[PDB]
Amino acid sequence: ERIPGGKFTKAQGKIVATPDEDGFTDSEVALALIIAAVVLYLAIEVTKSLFYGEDPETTAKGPMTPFEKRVVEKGLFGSRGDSYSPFRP
Amino acid sequence: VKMSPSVPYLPYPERLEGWVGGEKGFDPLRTSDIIDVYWLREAELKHGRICMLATLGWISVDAGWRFEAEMFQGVSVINAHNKMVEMGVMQQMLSIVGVCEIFSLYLIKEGLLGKIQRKAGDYFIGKNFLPKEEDKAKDMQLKELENGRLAMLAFSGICTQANLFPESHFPY
Amino acid sequence: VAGVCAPLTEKFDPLGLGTEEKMEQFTAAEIKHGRCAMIACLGYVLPEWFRFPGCESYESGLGALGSLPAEGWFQLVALIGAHEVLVKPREGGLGAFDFGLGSELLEGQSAEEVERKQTVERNNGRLAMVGFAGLVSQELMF
Amino acid sequence: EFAGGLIGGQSAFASQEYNFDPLGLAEKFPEQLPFFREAELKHGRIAMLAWVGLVVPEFVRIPGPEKCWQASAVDAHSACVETGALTQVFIFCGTLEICGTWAKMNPMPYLPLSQSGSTGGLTMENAGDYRLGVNFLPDEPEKVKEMKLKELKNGRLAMLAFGGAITQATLTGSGFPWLY
Amino acid sequence: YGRCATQRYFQVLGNIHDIELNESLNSPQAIQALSFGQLSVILLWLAAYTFHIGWSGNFEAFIDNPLGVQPINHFVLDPHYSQYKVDTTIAALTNHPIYHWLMTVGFTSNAQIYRFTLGLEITAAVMLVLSLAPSVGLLSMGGLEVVSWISICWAGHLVNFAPGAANLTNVVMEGPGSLGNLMNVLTFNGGIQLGTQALAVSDVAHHHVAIGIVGLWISALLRVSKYAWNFNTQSSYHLDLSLSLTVGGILTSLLAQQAYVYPALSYLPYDYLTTTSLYVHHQYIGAFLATGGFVHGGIFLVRDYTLSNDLVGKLLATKATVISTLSWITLFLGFHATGLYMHNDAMAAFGVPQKQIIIEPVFAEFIQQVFFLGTPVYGLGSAAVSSTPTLSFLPIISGGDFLVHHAIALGLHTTVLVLIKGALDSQGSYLFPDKQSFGYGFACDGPGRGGTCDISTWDSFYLAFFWVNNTVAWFTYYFHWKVLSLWQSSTAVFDENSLYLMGWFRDYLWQNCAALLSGYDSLGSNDLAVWAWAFLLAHLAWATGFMFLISWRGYWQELIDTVIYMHLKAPFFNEIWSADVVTPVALSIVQARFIGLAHYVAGFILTYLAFVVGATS
Amino acid sequence: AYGDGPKKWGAVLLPLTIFGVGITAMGTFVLYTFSEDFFWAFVPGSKRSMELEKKKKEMAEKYPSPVVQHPADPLAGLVNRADYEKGLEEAWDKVKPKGSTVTVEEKLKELSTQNNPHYWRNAIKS
Ligand code: CLA
Ligand code: CLA
Ligand code: CLA
Ligand SMILES: CC(=O)O[C@H]1CC(C)(C)C(=C=C/C(C)=C/C=C/C(C)=C/C=C/C=C(C)/C=C/C=C(C)/C=C/[C@@]23O[C@]2(C)C[C@@H](O)CC3(C)C)[C@](C)(O)C1
Ligand SMILES: CC(=O)O[C@H]1CC(C)(C)C(=C=C/C(C)=C/C=C/C(C)=C/C=C/C=C(C)/C=C/C=C(C)/C=C/[C@@]23O[C@]2(C)C[C@@H](O)CC3(C)C)[C@](C)(O)C1
Ligand SMILES: CC1=C(C/C=C(\C)CCC[C@H](C)CCC[C@H](C)CCCC(C)C)C(=O)c2ccccc2C1=O
């Protein structure tokens, strides 16, 4: 039970109807937590990748894909430049 | 000028060279150039294996080889998934497939990042049935890939034909 | 430094117990215990939420020792023992814990990353050992 | 020279070639000319098949759902789209077109031409060359050129023939003779 | 290790995301990876909201009676609550239109919400995976074509979940059919549809498909305009970032305006608090994005621009004219708005409210009557009445709105003046001719040449952010009081008392704080107790910002030196702490200014949020 | 009931998520302060950053890039710096003040040389 505060809550008479049951049970909450744990593992991987930066051999020892080769050659998709610009064209 | 043998008028998709099925060079809409062939081959093998199993599953359960337990008897292949999803059976199969696919996620991530050096589709189950001869090993891999492709198309067929004509069985 | 990660800085031997020679065998014992404890914690958690059709009668936890006809318990023990006696360490393994399973993932992995995987395994096994100890003692006593 | 040395400008009479381009599109767009020949040959082939498929059903028709097959040419298309025949024909033609032309033309078929540009896969030499039935070509360049010219002339004739046939059939109806 | 000072923290943390200075991940692939990680964080935040709405929330009870139920955000489990407060509180209520958005986009169950949370977590995992592998290939992803395709797909979703989709005959299978068949899911009725009191879902879906198609066409046109006249002469991450930030700020401010006046979420206007919070929040976000556009323009000038005879060179050459004219505009607007407000204050105070200077906003009234209104409300410009009018929530302006809009113009022009002045003087002033060699942010140039406090280009943003917050406060006070008068049906208390600023105090701030302050007192505490507590907390943060802004370093450095002396002379601790490890030093001047600004704006935002909640509850 | 659910999950996680997670974050950040790689990318001359720069140089000199890159030394862009200077020399001799004794190579050496020992990359004995 709540003590209403604010003129509009009293005037409009909106009631905070609590659902009878919970809504997510416990099994589906566990599944959400598992998926969040996988996302956390991926986030740890991303953090380790970004903190130590990109190693110099990759992008230098790994040959560019033919798509990347042709894009850099023709200057597309932000290449032939020094910007990111996700909203390029 | 390699002129991929499958589509003669198209240039060979260069990154397919050296892979098991690359001698036919069938990648029009060349996607090996945009996507790493490691990921493409892992996806192809996963689809092929899932379909090689799902084909046999659909055939066996449509013929009438239901499991021992009740809640498995009298359930057709079509209205099977919606049934075992409320019987609690699809949840545990999803759990097992989930741990297998977390293994798969680790393998794909580490392989693409270059940390591990496994081959695409190699989950280290086997390696004592591989023919141990490099030509024969590549032949076995090609057999797996061709059977997986045939099974992908076959399961697509079987499923669509069954669901379009519910009153039928495997010959369709 | 296989087990030493970061909460420590050195070997945790208050009662000096490794002192060479024993250290390798104790490492095998600890790694096996950690693996068993990790899978045992997973076991405690999951049967409470799904039950493997055919097993939806037995009680979980230590009560499963009472339930699950002793023939079935002996079959589980037979599988475990068949593995334990019939697997053996591989060959050029890092120790008696190297039973070859997944060792392909260590091929050309650098010393730091191989040791990091080792330490992750061992620390997770230690946490799972204390976790199972808590689970079993809590289920039994209270 | 005229139209980058493409085949098709030859006249029937003699070495006095036709070279029909009153609006001069070949000179104005020489780098877009392989695309022009691709479009011309594609339209010609489609029109050959289309005129043949306007003539043949007046003689023999496949058994089918009786709404698309047992219909005249002009009113066939709508009923065939409804019956699900032309949707499968579209699936087939779309797969063929995407793979073949969209990969021979776009070096990045996974990207629209607004993003890939290029379009250098269509050269002047391999304009209509989809490598289909090339063993039937005569083994000398002169007769290869003559056969390509035959294909182009028949394709243009089929374009005009299909246009006239469909227009007359809409105006009148009838069968193979689309006269009143 | 760690033989640095505490200054190291605030020195690196101020540039911790200045990846251009981070030589490791300096490539644009790394910046795209940062974008992927940020989008993963956004997806997880939306997953948070959806998960707590579906877990402990009344969405299933909300779809049934959207007018009579208050949306629940999450369950409150604070251990500090007293049993009564525990019995008092049900759960944390909702201050955002996520219930309305979910209802609009077709959610009808908590199972759908749970699947949405799972999908959001999976998409965040996908974003993290994409960030794991930066690559020129991934730089292909994006573009106006991609965002237009996203708009088209959203149109498809809205078509699939439009209320009339049940009556829709399958177009792709049975043909387009009659026009009404398409009207089941694609409409252009225009304006509020009555009932839900929001734009029809068919209208939104049709809007999105049209916008996506037009965006595809516009992107193709822009790229052919790049075919001929291909000139990427000035590429900089800060130039493109400024472009994106300015466009995003314009779009967000437009979103606030057109979402108040054309709500797209069903049963949203019935919820006053969520509407007010939406408008205020989006206007603050838009102003912040515009300020960021100006800031990154200044940064591009500082360290990425090379002088040429181009657009920017022309702007720089006549920067004195720009600054002088902006100063004149601001002086005129401030003088006249303040003087008219003071004149109205004097007239109302002296019991002569008729003698106030009320300049009727005849130009905006002319625009409204001629272009927007369908009935003669003012009668100037046009008096025609529309036979079939459409509905919306466009306010009817009066005399006070003229002065308020002039205050808004003063605020915007002063903010632009500060930002433009700082950006263009980043190239140098006669007090600091060589600012091109000192970087975007620095303390000062010392006491010489008469003094050089706040002479840095970053200090220009520091000064202009107060003006950003002040301008947003001005027009959000305007919006909040206007909608409060409209909802309370006064509409004459506003139109008369907004002419003089004592009205803005008494009838707006003092009047609307009555319920908020009673959140907790000797009698007890109600649901507004949390907001009174946050009100006080925000005031405390604001005054701490005052501390960091007024008092400067040297004093505090000497005080900290004496405190270090006390520690080194203290017993039982000189054996342990020699001040060599992370030496405690006073915050640098730039760090102090930023932290004071941060406390100032944090108190600003939290104070106004608490006030809005306590006033529109 | 409605309360159950978030009550038990909260009693488990909220102590964890706030106390354990925040305290661990604070302690690990204090450790990171005393770590060798503390803000390594933003501390000039840090060991990790210098090793990364050295390895970048090694990769650049071992795997030449077909595309032209922004020259770290602006004069290193020249395809033939010899021709650059030879031209300068010719132009300077054309516009030399009378028989000046100043030559182009000496001027280039004088302009290129600089005595800034306090600039880093020079305080690291480099
Ligand atoms: C099966 C149990 C077991 C075994 C055999 C080992 C074995 C080992 N651990 Mg280890 N460890 C364990 C459990 C175990 N651990 C657990 C649960 C934790 C979590 C706290 C740790 C944490 C840990 C750290 C942090 C480190 C080790 C290290 C080591 C190695 C050297 C230590 C040594 O010589 O002692 C081996 C012998 C024993 C551990 C005796 C086990 C049986 C004793 C007698 C039990 C004593 C009572 C115990 C508290 C149980 C409570 C019940 C009691 C009230 C009756 C060795 C390989 C070191 C290492 O890796 O070297 C680099 C190291 O730094 N361990
Ligand atoms: C997508 C948009 C975007 C992007 C990518 C960037 C990117 C960048 N900006 Mg930028 N900026 C933006 C928008 C953006 N900005 C906007 C909108 C503004 C205007 C507000 C600015 C204003 C701005 C300035 C003034 C500066 C930058 C700078 C930078 C660069 C370094 C960032 C850094 O390390 O800051 C460090 C980031 C922080 C210290 C974050 C502060 C943490 C906040 C304040 C926590 C407080 C919230 C707290 C939880 C509230 C508690 C409430 C209380 C009641 C409890 C980097 C390239 C800097 C630069 O390039 O200088 C060379 C610089 O000086 N930006
Ligand atoms: C109430 C507080 C207040 C006031 C009045 C001002 C006023 C002003 N600020 Mg300002 N500022 C403030 C707080 C304030 N600031 C704070 C807290 C910050 C954060 C540090 C800033 C940061 C800031 C920056 C960074 C800039 C300004 C600028 C300006 C000027 C803008 C031009 C203008 O509006 O002229 C109107 C002037 C007034 C309203 C002052 C009052 C004048 C009289 C009393 C009112 C009129 C009475 C009547 C008409 C005169 C009678 C005439 C005759 C009968 C005698 C103006 C003098 C800009 C500037 O100087 O550009 C020109 C500029 O660049 N300010
Ligand atoms: C190549 C091939 O073919 O196969 C390969 C595949 C692959 C994947 C590559 C491989 C691998 C790796 C694997 C299999 C990794 C599995 C790791 C697991 C299962 C770890 C579990 C930890 C559980 C913990 C810490 C529990 C902790 C529990 C705690 C802290 C519980 C604590 C409390 O319970 C206690 C104590 C009291 C309770 O009341 C309260 C709570 C909190 C629940 C292999 C081995 O290479 C084999
Ligand atoms: C490996 C492999 O597989 O080999 C393959 C390779 C490859 C290349 C695909 C092959 C081929 C070639 C093919 C398939 C060639 C087919 C060519 C066709 C069908 C040409 C039709 C022309 C119709 C015309 C001009 C209609 C003309 C109609 C006219 C002028 C009609 C004109 C009027 O109708 C109009 C306009 C009005 C009417 O009222 C009156 C009339 C006058 C009748 C191979 C060798 O085969 C097999
Ligand atoms: C109060 C004040 C200080 C003193 C404030 C300081 C030194 C910062 C206060 C630190 C707070 C109290 C946290 C102290 C450390 C905490 C234990 C958190 C540590 C976090 C790190 C581990 C990252 C200044 O240095 C200063 C400098 C320039 C102008 C004005 C002022 C000013 O007003």
Image (spheres, coloured by chain):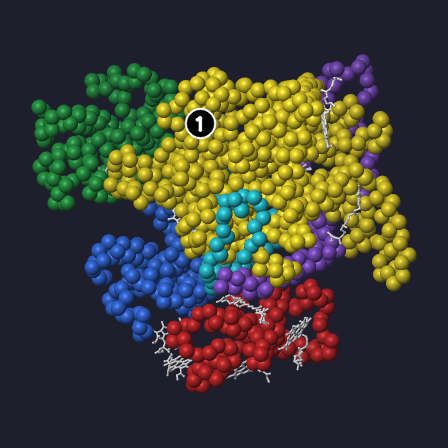
Chain colours: A cyan, B blue, C red, D green, E yellow, F purple
Q: Is residue B157 above or below residue F122?
A: below
User: Which image quarter holds the C terminus of chain E?
Assistant: top right
Residue at the far bottom in the pictured view: C70
Residue at the far right in the pictured view: E569
State which chain disc 1 sits on: E
Q: Position of residue C12 (x, y in %)?
A: 71, 72
Q: Name the residue beneath numbered marker 1.
A: E221
Q: Residue at x 50, y 42 (%)?
A: E271
Q: Position of residue E178 (x, y in %)?
A: 26, 35
Residue flagged by tag 1: what amino acid is it? Leu
Q: Position of residue D1 (x, y in %)?
A: 35, 19
Closest to the observer: D121 or E170?
Answer: E170
Q: Position of residue E343 (x, y in %)?
A: 69, 22
Q: Is residue C54 visible?
A: yes
> In the picture provided, is E357 more to the left or to the right than D146?
right
> In the picture provided, is B119 more to the left or to the right than E189?
right
Q: Residues within 10 Å of mark 1 (few under 14, many from 20)?
A: some
Say which quarter of the image contains residue E417.
Answer: top right
User: Which image quarter holds the N terminus of chain E?
Assistant: bottom right
- SS for dot 1: helix
Closest to the observer: B26 or E51?
Answer: E51
Q: Residue at x 13, y 43 (%)?
A: D66
Q: Is residue B112 visible?
A: no
